Image 1 (cartoon, rainbow over the protein chains, first blue to last red):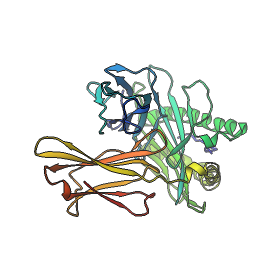
Image 2: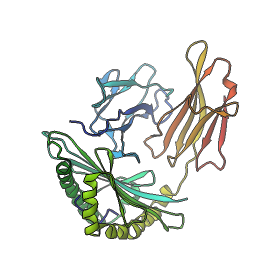
Image 3: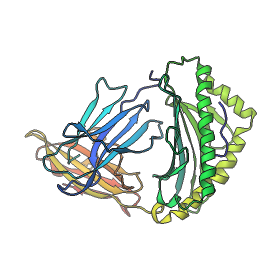
Image 4: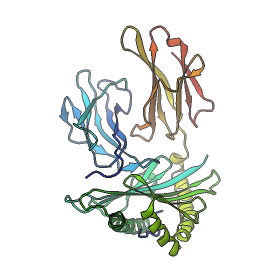
Length: 9
Length: 103
Length: 274
């Protein structure tokens, strides 16, 4: 299952 | 426009199974340990680029260096020669590695 | 033994030749099971192992949404990194991400990972405690401060100990016929004359799974650490792996050398002699 959250650097 | 420490690909050309003339097999070219990921890989038969060649999805190792597998079904014979051709920013000219049934 | 799930994503800019390309792959141990390619036509997370195809349509919808959102985020991250470093738009740059978890034989969480590399070098990584970050340079410290303020590590800890472990446990059950196997290496030795004074002894390991393996040569019981040629472990294409190791031996001294093979599918390590 893929991460539910990405975020900006 | 390459960026970051360059790493030359390590190239291996080999069959999936020990070669037997007249017996269907797979010809592989595995390129690993390279950066950046932009690369050209072809399989050759008697010096000519093979058309229907598949490849794995770009992935990378723990040290972040990239690897790819290029492969095609083939039936080896005693006379036919095969090779892998690789072009990469680290290579002054394309590198052609011939298939040797004993590597 | 233990098992792992990993996702690997690569974002590459190609100035003047299109917009950046995003590729993501998912693995359980050494077996790939999904992929996404932003250049490809489907625009979906796609199966790459038989045992994942039984997942229903809402798996594929949910996984597609998550990976497409990551694709867009890391494309913007390439822009941000360019700015942080004041690098020119002329250069092609790379952003890699890896995340995933390890579980033991009993399914318990053993380790979580969530880390980035920029142009092939560490950028930022979640520490083993899943509470703090390791930033590799002054740009990554800007990111570290931002992620500390937004409590990103809390969300990634929750994913790694929860969703990640749950998915890996389920994949291991659904693909158990295939993922919980060990194929031991088939071994042999070949002999290749160079001159009339030297020949190559090559020790082979074929058809093994998983890929982790150790091949070493000894001479009279003493290791040949520096005179051995060891190729990278390579895929056969059928789910197994191959590797060889070679030593150059003075003609007539073949019987002084032994090859030693360690693999988790072998109840005891092997010793081969020509």
